[PDB]
Image: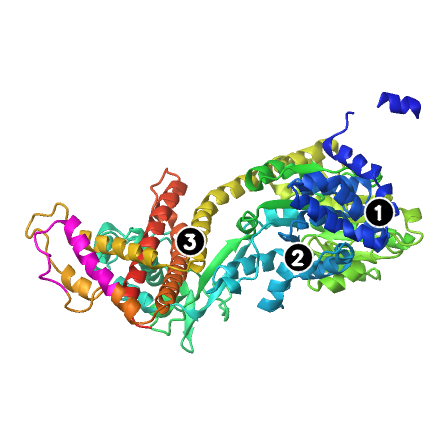
Amino acid sequence: HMLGILNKRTLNRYEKIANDIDAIRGDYENLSDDALKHKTIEFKERLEKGATTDDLLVEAFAVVREASRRVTGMFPFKVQLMGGVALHDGNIAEMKTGEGKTLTSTLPVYLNALTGKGVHVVTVNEYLASRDAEQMGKIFEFLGLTVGLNLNSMSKDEKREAYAADITYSTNNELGFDYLRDNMVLYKEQMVQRPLHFAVIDEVDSILIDEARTPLIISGQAAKSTKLYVQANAFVRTLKAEKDYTYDIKTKAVQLTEEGMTKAEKAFGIDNLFDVKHVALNHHINQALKAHVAMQKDVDYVVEDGQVVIVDSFTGRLMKGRRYSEGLHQAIEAKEGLEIQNESMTLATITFQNYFRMYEKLAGMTGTAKTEEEEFRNIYNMQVVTIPTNRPVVRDDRPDLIYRTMEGKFKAVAEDVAQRYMTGQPVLVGTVAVETSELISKLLKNKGIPHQVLNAKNHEREAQIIEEAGQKGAVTIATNMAGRGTDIKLGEGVKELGGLAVVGTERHESRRIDNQLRGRSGRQGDPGITQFYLSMEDELMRRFGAERTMAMLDRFGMDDSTPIQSKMVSRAVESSQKRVEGNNFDSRKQLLQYDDVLRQQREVIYKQRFEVIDSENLREIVENMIKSSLERAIAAYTPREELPEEWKLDGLVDLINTTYLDEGALEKSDIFGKEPDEMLELIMDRIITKYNEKEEQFGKEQMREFEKVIVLRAVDSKWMDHIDAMDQLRQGIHLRAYAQTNPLREYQMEGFAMFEHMIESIEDEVAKFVMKAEI
């Protein structure tokens, strides 16, 4: 009281803000709905007059907190206010399951939506997106904000409207696909998304760590060309057994030699087969070579009904739908003189990781993220903030039990479930593969135990099951990807029984997943128990330290009769797991360096394309592209040194009359013995008037749209070729790098050169199509 006041801090940033907000709870506690809602108007006026979101945080959060009580009956706990602050700061709020992370997100989302820039609230699937938008939307709407829901089944117009709302719920995949489609648009008005401001990502460790490289692709409705498969096949029939190409015994590796390589360059009229402009041609030759030397008809595959069908080596049985990949199947089709069925072309591509890094601000929520903090910081510039549970956790997380065999492990699992079920205490069995769930389910069926199986196929249906998994007598088997996002509340008389009992059937590649399974139980201080069952036969048990220990326990004489539960063993297993995570992280970091190459090129290309779309006058840009294009053409026929047997032979004449100027427009005009510097300006002048002509003479503003379309088609077309070539370059980078050397550098350098190739290709196309084409 007075002693307290006189004394009145060692509290952290989040506890402080939390108390502040709690301190002014009375200033809204009795305000009127209309008046509480008007607060939104007040906040926007203040932001208009210089206020920041950080300035309004305390009050904004207090407002939402109150609004939540009225709309849902829930008054955000203080730990939730702390979570909201962490998310608002652009970091990850690690909140355990059952802490109400969803209501928590309404705090920073409301705050960051006031400036009318939009806020994306991302969920793993559309069921959760629609549920949350429906339930949480009532709060935002109570406060005068609009809530949108972006679904795959929605048309462009409906999507655009959902994106125009103050807040937009969606899934990681749809947001990415919309982004790719917005960047293939012919008119800026066709886009559906607004600039990417702020995204609040649920299950952020899953999305940005585990599924970070998830590919989002937009394929071409049209088909690729087969001509190159034909030519490549024709060429390969010319080569000899040893001095034209090699062939390893052990592996099916088939490589070309200098003779073959010289022969190829000779045959295809090129100087360097390894030149980035020829990556496709080189890839096709390697595949046709492989098709003739490493693939045998009637042993590897068969030809039936005009098609190549893969033969299962050891059964002799056919695998009708399967196809070899990376063009090898088409190469074989060409070899066998069959109809070549080429793949569809990728028009646009991106990963979860690189899509989200396009946002101005990012926040995330998960009960498991602290361990990956360094990765979140370096990659997404997000820190991880551990948020205290509202109530102490009294869940009893038992140490792993280790059996000698899978059989014993599973039997012990079924036995455990049976005992729990006999008492009525609810049980949830976690598994990693659907095949494992069915293994356990059959064990439970033989014991006459009623139970539910979640395989993560129908989310709405599974959410309904999960919601009842805490009821007396309940027995649920779920694959780690099932039932996510739905709390399991204890039914009447359940806590008295011990709360939810969770049984793990095996350790996951990441401890984060083990703990998410553990977290389904013991919410809000509820009692509970978790137990992982393992065996010496498990994948992890055959790793690092786990290996030597199991070997020792084996010789010691361990049986399934009595499992091992030792702190020494448990820590050795923990050590292996940490090492497994260590290696997975090294791999990720390696893949990040390779992914970064195409990533930067895409951000650049898209940035440029947008400008083309967002431009009224493009002639300057087009003229420059012609300039550059012509300069390369002139330089091509003006050997800066060549004296031997000619000294600048001339063919550029017809090459210009066929590419820029009309047929027979120049030749005797200032072209002869002149200087490259001169020949350039002279020919350009002709081009200008030639452009002025076609411009004003034919069509008025049609010229500006004539360009607009020619440039967009060139960008999109060349970007398409670039993606395919960069993919081939990456797959075969080891063939371009010398042994005892890191291919990453070679990939970076060749990737840079290919990008140059793409720009020059874009300039040439736009050059010809504008100087030689009518609408």
Q: Which residues are magenta?
A: 666-691
Residue 196 point in image, percent of width and height: 57, 51
Q: Secondary structure at mark 2?
A: strand
Q: Which residue is mark 3?
A: 608
Badge 3: few (under 14), some or many (20 or more) residues near its Cα, within 10 Å?
few
- Image mark for residue 75: 1
- Distance from the alpha carbon under mark 2 to that under mark 3: 27 Å
Q: Which residue is mark 2?
A: 168
677 in the magenta segment: yes
Q: Nearer the viewer, residue 407 or 449?
A: 449
Q: Is residue 537 visible?
A: no
Image coords of residue 639 (percent x, y): 14, 49
Residue found at x 79% / y 35%: 20
Residue 542 locus on image (x, y percent): 61, 42
Distance CA(mark 3)–CA(mark 1): 48 Å
Percent across and percent down for residue 220 are 45, 67
* Residue density around tag 2, few if under 14, some if 14–19, many if 20 or more, within 10 Å: many
Question: Between marks 1 and 2, how big is the CA–CA gap?
Answer: 23 Å
Identify the residue shown where x is 53% and y is 43%: 588
